[PDB]
Image: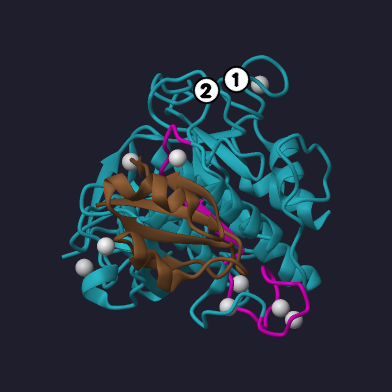
Chain colours: A brown, B cyan
Amino acid sequence: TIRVIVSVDKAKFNPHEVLGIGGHIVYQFKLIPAVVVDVPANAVGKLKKMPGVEKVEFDHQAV
Amino acid sequence: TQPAQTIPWGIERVKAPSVWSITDGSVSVIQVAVLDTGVDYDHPDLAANIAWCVSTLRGKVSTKLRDCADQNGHGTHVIGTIAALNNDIGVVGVAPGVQIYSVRVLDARGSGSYSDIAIGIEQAILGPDGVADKDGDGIIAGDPDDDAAEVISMSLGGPADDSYLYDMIIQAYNAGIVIVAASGNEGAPSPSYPAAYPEVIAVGAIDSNDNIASFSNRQPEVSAPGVDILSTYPDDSYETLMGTAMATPHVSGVVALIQAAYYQKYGKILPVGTFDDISKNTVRGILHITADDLGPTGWDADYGYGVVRAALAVQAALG
Ligand SMILES: [Ca+2]
Ligand SMILES: [Ca+2]
Ligand SMILES: [Ca+2]
Ligand SMILES: [Ca+2]
Ligand SMILES: [Ca+2]
Ligand SMILES: [Ca+2]
Ligand SMILES: [Ca+2]
Ligand SMILES: [Zn+2]
Ligand SMILES: [Zn+2]
Ligand SMILES: [Zn+2]
């Protein structure tokens, strides 16, 4: 699994449907239209075409 | 048993003690959110200023103490620089009476993910009541009806830019909240993110001879004491460290003092201001024009505007 952050269109995107591609929801932001999701490394391309998905961004580490 | 109080040189350097007769930061509406490794929450020289203890590690928001405690020391040290109490023991912070929201976004290693950090910012904005703007008036930082922090302090950074992190920083900026971040420790030509956003004050590090530290990422917005910094450290102890992580809380303590002294006098807080600002009408304008202008005149790539000075910033704010 990798963890990505999906920018979403609220009125096209369904958090329950990331299961369709092997995914699950980690955290839905309240203040920004984005969601942290865990997904198979090879589902990122599928995730990118999911309805309501506007951008897929990857997680990074800070020191 | 606890040592007798000392004033770390960095506190003296940013001209904090002369403010404390006006305010030590303990104006009710003011809170500082420290996004870090957590906090030694029973530390005798910190306990009384910890108003809220949250954790966002692994995407999972927790108010449990197992989860909120410092397993590293980094957050305990940083927090002590802002807010170690003015009493008979240990050390003393820039704003030794300010309330702290310790928001644990970094793990036992002092390392953390962008997504936990972005959740951390949202949590600083939402406050313990889990609502940003409870009365729907548009005022969040400085509204005494809400519980948002007025300052977000981030002794962390990374080389990557993302719109999710960026949008969270716009949310905090728009909430009226002063954002402070370490410029980074790579000796690089420019700051790490989020310090590098125009919404965020990038802080660089000086040593005790007023030289910029060799590791300090350049092009900060201001600079502050960041080498040989004595502060609090687990368990119920003290340690001396260096890094822009140490410089950043000095600048957050100064900001809390401005906002706390301004509120106390006017019953409102100052606007955040811009990276460019040179007016006396915003927190950042005041920070710029009252900074000790070291090196080349005006903004320079080593020190930014100069070393922040609470005593003049606050005089200018009430002026
Ligand atoms: Ca302790
Ligand atoms: Ca003390
Ligand atoms: Ca709130
Ligand atoms: Ca409000
Ligand atoms: Ca209000
Ligand atoms: Ca507040
Ligand atoms: Ca200069
Ligand atoms: Zn998962
Ligand atoms: Zn990225
Ligand atoms: Zn660090």
Q: Are marks 2 and 1 in contact (CB under 8 Å)?
A: yes
Query: Residue A1, image x and y in percent?
Result: 24, 52
Task: Report the Cα–Cα distance between label 2 and label 1.
Answer: 5 Å
Which stretch did the figure color magenta?
B134-160
Marking on residue B218: 2
Answer with left or right where residue A23 lies relative to residue B26: left
Q: At 40% from the left edge and 19% from the top edge, which residue is drawn? A: B214
Q: Main secondary structure of the magenta part?
A: loop
Answer with left or right where residue B24 lies relative to residue B3: right
Q: At 68% from the left edge and 61% from the top edge, which residue is drawn? A: B259
Vertical relation: B2 (above or below) A16: above
Question: Circle 1 is placed at which residue position?
Answer: B301
Earlier sequence position, callout 2 versus callout 1: 2
Q: At 42% from the left edge and 75% from the top edge, which residue is drawn? A: B52
Answer with left or right where residue B39 lies relative to residue A45: left
Instruction: Tell me if I can see residue B289 in this picture.
Output: yes
Instruction: Tell me if I can see residue B16 in this picture.
Output: no
Quarter in which the N terminus of chain B is drawn: bottom left
Answer with the quarter of the image where residue B93 lies. bottom left
Query: Residue B192, image x and y in percent?
Result: 48, 33
